[PDB]
Image (cartoon, rainbow over all chains, first blue to last red; front, side, top):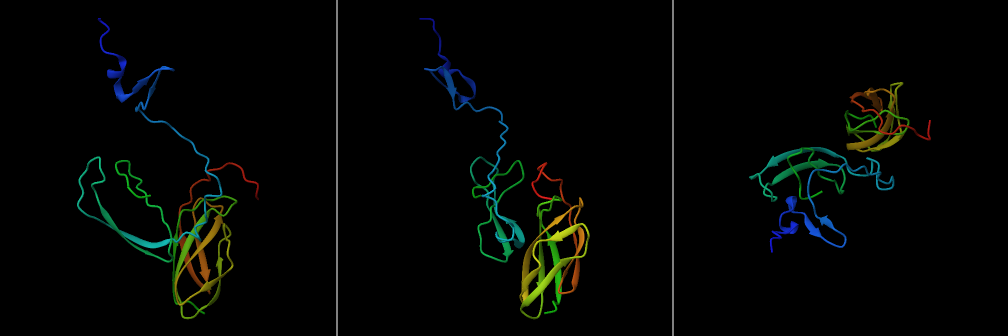
Length: 98
Length: 98
């Protein structure tokens, strides 16, 4: 009668408590360090992937938020047709395309 | 083919036994041929020897260096250009190559 609320409705960080065995699934907190030894086959020499002669960036209207609300345009000059990866090294910016 | 004007742009480089350095030569020449590319430094060695040269374009090449920095002159059909870089320490510890 005086059991109160269960731990499913009070666990912080939105951790879904399940039984058999007792555990907490999808418990988001902190960061995990991961070291990955990528196979040597994946890598390719720079002479194969098209190196780009230069690039210019022009950022369109943007709003800082959770969704991919910001947009930009890259003017690129290169030498061959390929499949470049695009990344942001800043901690406070992420890209939709990789 | 005696090239008219060439310039050097160095990508990420690393000083190790393996060919862990890459660079690009943007060249403007007058004929299609087979220029021999070379390095005029005792602390840097290229991979390719003879490169197909066009009228105008770019060529990507590889090199290995022993200095912490790439401060070395590269020659293409006689024309010399100083490539300036800054090579990081090698990530590995041992190689099965000399």
